[PDB]
């Protein structure tokens, strides 16, 4: 596995993901993943400025697992620095009932 394309659209290899916020200024997705992976296998791993991140699992449990297990952890950046990143699901006007 490597993946490498110019385009790189907003694809969702999975549905069960975990929103990470409160990342360091040096924090990366690599280390982040290696961390988030705590759950299971990460098919998606991205990080943005400010201090946010995103990881997608192949299993639901993994999500909840890492969600709780991790639920706010001490992430170490590639610069040694650290920061408290929370692990929570993604919400946005749920359907509830069609």
Image (cartoon, rainbow, N blue to C red):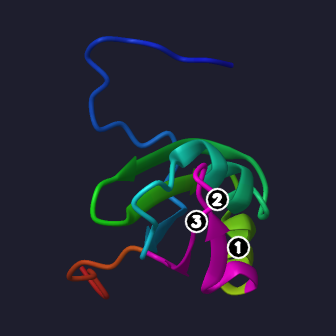
Q: Are marks 3 and 2 in contact (CB under 8 Å)?
A: yes
Q: Are marks 2 and 1 in contact (CB under 8 Å)?
A: no
Q: Secondary structure at mark 2?
A: loop
User: Badge 3, how many Cα within 10 Å: few under 14, some, many 20+?
Assistant: few
Residue drawn at the location 77% of the way across and 64% of the way down? 39
Counting residues from the start of the chain, the first of labels 2 and 1 encountered is 1
Q: 47 left or right of 9? A: right
Give me the C-alpha separation between circle 2 and circle 1: 22 Å
User: Badge 2, how many Cα within 10 Å: few under 14, some, many 20+?
Assistant: few
Q: 67 left or right of 13? A: right
Q: Secondary structure at mark 3?
A: loop
The mark lying in front, picked from 3 and 1, is: 3
User: Badge 1, how many Cα within 10 Å: few under 14, some, many 20+?
Assistant: many
Where is residue 54? Give x, y as percent. Answer: 45, 57
Mark drawn on residue 81? 3
Whether residue 8 is in magenta: the answer is: no
Give me the C-alpha separation between circle 3 and circle 1: 22 Å
Q: 28 left or right of 37? A: left
Q: Which residue was labeled with disc 1?
A: 66
Where is residue 75? Give x, y as percent. Answer: 63, 69
Q: Are marks 3 and 1 in contact (CB under 8 Å)?
A: no
Counting residues from the start of the chain, the first of labels 3 and 1 encountered is 1
Mark drawn on residue 80? 2
């Amino acid at each position: 596995g490597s993946s490498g394309s110019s385009g790189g659209p907003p694809t969702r290899r999975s549905d069960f993901r975990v929103l990470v916020s409160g990342l360091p200024p040096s924090g990366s997705w690599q280390d982040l993943k290696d961390h988030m992976r705590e759950a299971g296998d990460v098919c998606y791993a991205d990080v943005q400025k400010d201090g946010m991140g995103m990881v997608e699992y192949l299993r639901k449990e993994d999500m909840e697992y890492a969600l709780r297990k991790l639920d706010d952890t001490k992430f170490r950046s590639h610069e040694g620095e650290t920061s408290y990143i929370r692990v929570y699901p993604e919400r946005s006007s749920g359907p509830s009932s069609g």
